[PDB]
Length: 220
Length: 220
Ligand SMILES: O=C(COP(=O)(O)O)[C@H](O)[C@H](O)COP(=O)(O)O
Image 1: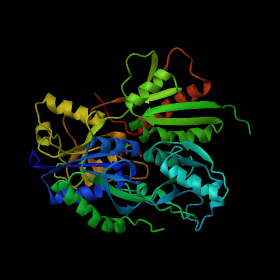
Image 2: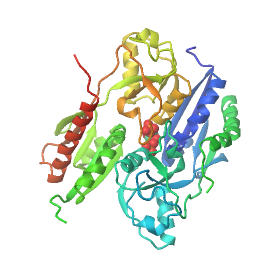
Image 3: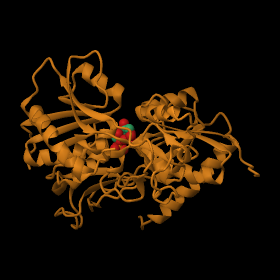
Image 4: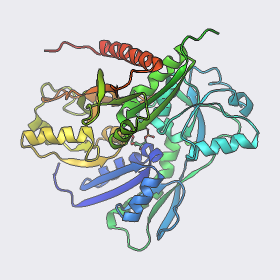
């Protein structure tokens, strides 16, 4: 091992993408051991500020931002799904109706959050009331709250793929889910990508569908 | 239908406490269904602001803050430890020196993090240069990077697992580790705790000493 790294890769990704980006960083760093990587993980507001200040090589976001000279490339599905404990009575039920589901307590992200609005918007179309027991601003906090028995959640499928994930939390088979959403690679269009970043972007675009199969992203 | 405990409970905790606090709310609410609980998860600057504005009943942080009239209750040790993959050559080695550890690449959190600054200060105290090859802003990313073979990390004990996931990490026996850090519940001392807050605090102390007993080892 060497102390000085002839090249650097600066990434900033939306919080939920923390479960997926390291699956690329790992094999990339094994191929190019002379690179040091910096990875920032933050919400949409944080990422916009970093783009505004031009801090990183590459950004991973859900929705492409307005007001910036950027190139945007979709690369991966981010489906939102119903999550609960494996011990829940509905855990193994097939085709759970949205009515049987609405009578369940939920732990969701804050109002105005992407996942929260999707389930609220969906619950509006069937004129049903969503029973919100607790509002948490963190994927990890929500999953901890589920295993404490406080109810079910709507989370991105990628929160189920933590390293060493166990069958203790599981995706529920529910009508109207998964709700399709996408992740995009974003970078400033005014300046050319560095060689390291361009090499990583190509890897991300060519390698992500292999990983999508290995973690079994639902195409639903 | 006789609930002796009804009230409002407002909690605010430092980010790392998302790994132990939200899972406790579940059984607490199952025991006291008449208590309405809100939980805010934020960083140190955010938490300090909330204490200043008197927004919550109880606050969970590591080091007690300066400049506030507060009562402080210790409740859980969350020590910092060296972790690597089980297949690493050092995995089963006894009494690894910091010199020996310093030849390895490290995967750490960003600057300003508790784990990063503790590790930088310790290695500086032995005039050792820490090879931080990957600076990753997420424990989940760090754990994947470890399992990918990219090197070693420093994490707090309760971050070594996550809700529904037990990655195959191994704690290394290393001189200068574990670095003890104590977590505290704090509340303004000018006002008596509300009945519900005192009930939650008593619960938090009882369940944390349960966790402490479960991992107890001989100390000096
Ligand atoms: O911004 C967040 C949101 O929390 P969450 O990931 O729980 O949605 C976290 O700081 C990073 O994601 C890293 O979290 P971690 O160190 O736990 O991986």
